[PDB]
Amino acid sequence: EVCSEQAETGPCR
Amino acid sequence: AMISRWYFDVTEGKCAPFFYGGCGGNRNNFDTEEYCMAVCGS
Amino acid sequence: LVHGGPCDKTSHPYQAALYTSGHLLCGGVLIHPLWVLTAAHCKKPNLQVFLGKHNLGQQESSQEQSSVVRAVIHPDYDAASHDQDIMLLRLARPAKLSELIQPLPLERDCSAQTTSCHILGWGKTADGDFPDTIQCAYIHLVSREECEHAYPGQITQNMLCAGDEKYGKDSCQGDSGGPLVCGDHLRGLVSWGNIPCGSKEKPGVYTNVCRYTNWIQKTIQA
Amino acid sequence: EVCSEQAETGPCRAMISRWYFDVTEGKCAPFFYGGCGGNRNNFDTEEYCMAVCG
């Protein structure tokens, strides 16, 4: 389920 | 980068803003609160 | 801000500058395209807001200016005690977001455990200068018990303490209303602290933003 | 006496233009008030400062 995934700022932050 | 995006927060039951870096991450990542709630809202 | 250094140009898109009669009065935080948060003791008639600024001494292509069209000071603000030191400012039109203008998410959880934060502002520096280039400093949240020991009888649930015991990094005059940023969320607003500025002995005191979730959203929804 | 007190920013962190009577200068002078507290040698205008302390 996509909606239960953590918020991920990702590696370009 | 620092770009304001939206994700569905299961502890609040609704979407919330977060700073996205502009690349990678995952799919719980929407450019508006409306789009987030249309996909993940109850 | 004392004992800090210049921020990177792209690391503060949510920082506002509040001007009165052509000079800096306070900092502030863009939290919504129409709304800037600041400290209630920053209230004055006919304020101008600058967004997208880095160096106050020059005109910047990224900057956007707006009059405040509506000021909403917290109804329970008590100046004598610094309690509930928060104010909302409505801009004349929605800010155009960019690389250098973005709203900062609010901390909604008063139990958030991130204690590693930073402050920023154009306020007074350690040698008394007022910088043109916005300054930045990393600091940490201080426990409420340690906070109350520093200022006995003064710390309410609507206040939060933060500082740096090694260098005394701290906010100072001109920084009021600027952000205490923890985990990419707005945790506090610059409010008051020790005289002289510096947090080696007594931390800076910040408006506890997580307490104002519902007041903020209610005010924004008209 | 109020007009002999040092100019005090107080503990709040705003930059508000105010006026205080400077004893050695013999006249009122600007200073930046923090927005809360301080003392009574602190006036909105130069004229009102000089009207009280001059």
Image (cartoon, coloured by chain):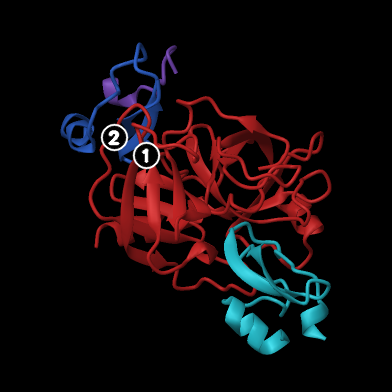
Chain colours: A purple, B blue, C red, D cyan
> Where is mark 1, residue-wise?
C103
Chain-order first, disc 1 or disc 2: 2
As displayed, is residue C88 above or below residue D4?
Answer: above
Q: Name the image quarter holding the C terminus of chain C.
A: bottom left
Which residue is tagged 2?
A: C97
Q: Nearer the viewer, residue C108 or C220?
A: C220
Percent position of residue C204, x then y? 69, 50
Q: Quadrant of residue B39?
A: top left
Query: Is residue C194 something that shows in the picture?
Result: yes
Using residue C108 as the reference point, say whether residue D12 is left or right of it.
right
Q: Residue at x 71, y 56 (%)?
A: C193
The reply to whether residue C114 is in sight is no
Confirm or deny contact between disc 1 and disc 2 (CB under 8 A).
yes
Q: Residue at x 29, y 45 (%)?
A: C33
Quadrant where the image shows the N terminus of chain C: top right
Q: Which amino acid does the dot numbered 1 rest on?
A: Pro
When the figure is inspected, residue C50 is found, relative to residue B29, above or below; the finding is below
